[PDB]
Length: 37
Image (cartoon, helix red, strand yellow):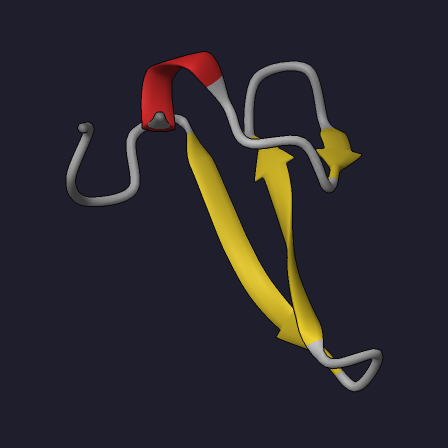
């Protein structure tokens, strides 16, 4: 139940959903982060 962007940032793409980007690893995944679950 993590609130507020911690390490990850999500943007909603014209595909109609949000993708999660981790600012340390520079990784973009559609899977919900552990530190943002």
